[PDB]
Length: 326
DNA sequence: CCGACAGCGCATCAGC
DNA sequence: GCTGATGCGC
DNA sequence: GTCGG
Ligand SMILES: O=c1ccn([C@H]2C[C@H](O)[C@@H](COP(=O)(O)NP(=O)(O)OP(=O)(O)O)O2)c(=O)[nH]1
Ligand SMILES: [Cl-]
Ligand SMILES: [Cl-]
Ligand SMILES: [Cl-]
Ligand SMILES: [Cl-]
Ligand SMILES: [Mg+2]
Ligand SMILES: [Mg+2]
Ligand code: NA
Ligand code: NA
Image 1 (cartoon, rainbow, N blue to C red):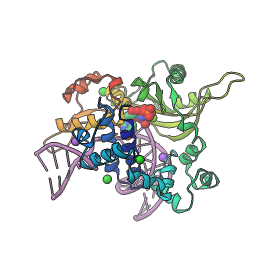
Image 2 (cartoon, rainbow, N blue to C red):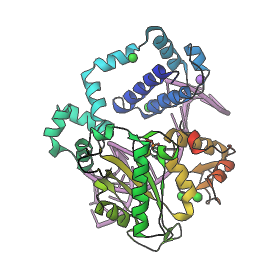
Image 3 (tube, chains in turn brown, green, cyan, orange):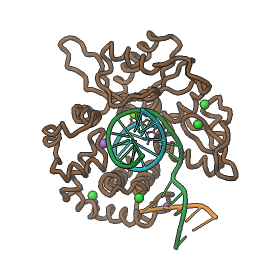
Image 4 (tube, rainbow, N blue to C red):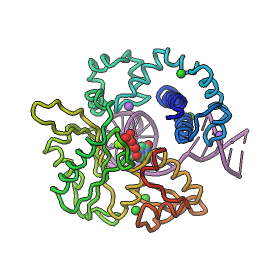
């Protein structure tokens, strides 16, 4: 955290462009800049020094100079003092409420947590659950609790069918000491790119996890992706653990590596890797890596037997999960 | 200067 | 009912 | 907002 003040600023700017300005490219520009500076091993002394890094342009260089000199950014000072912007940024912190819905509610006068609770009828299912656990979803999950959750999920899945393989990905797989949520990759031999020999593969797992009262709510659910809420069991006389967000993704077993690569992230790392892939003549998604024909159209899936194989195709030295936190 | 900026699942809606 | 566009999230 | 060509 040598340049914590600077990356925080960029992150706030990014959030402003996404939530308030609805300028997604600026949002990603600020995030990339924050990401490149976050791994820079020196305490930045000036915007010029920063401009040397890829992703940091003139505009950001000037802001970094203003920040280093005064310790703040006038542009952000004003944004903070602006009711509308402040309200919109806040409402987007509720899962299910995005920039559009946030601005829509703010236009209706609904701009505080209190307002949301009294107008619960104006929220869809997801937003309603996000509001319900607003506080809990803000807390981090210690890795020790993640290990507990992992044991529960792997053991409950095993009980449904010994052939299932549940892998915890996301920040957890990257070795994080704390995670925002739990991300679970799921595979079963009956579900491949060639066929789905068994229906409800994801449903059954969800069902079992709900039966043992691990999963408490559902935000969204389909044939291959479950988005919900879970909670560790507490002991007698013991205070209850906070409710946690849990994501489960069922991927074709023969496409596990592209899947675990995707789900392990980070998101910025995935963006960088997928962008680099293109420059090399390939396109990567969570299922496959395909070559790009002279017309730009994606060819057929290339053989893959490990995460490393994907890195080789794009001429990138393999990077352990723990080093993909960009 | 200009176009590119990663890729996709689920929920909701408009138009038919 | 369907398809396609859009919002939101991973 | 930044970048390559
Ligand atoms: O925009 C996105 C979001 C997520 N992802 C992938 C990578 C990410 O690591 C994974 C899980 O998403 P989360 O939002 O759960 N993030 P992560 O687990 O990395 O961190 P956190 O501790 O915040 O959950 O999904 C993308 O590829 N693109
Ligand atoms: Cl933009
Ligand atoms: Cl500031
Ligand atoms: Cl694969
Ligand atoms: Cl594909
Ligand atoms: Mg996660
Ligand atoms: Mg997640
Ligand atoms: Na730069
Ligand atoms: Na939100």
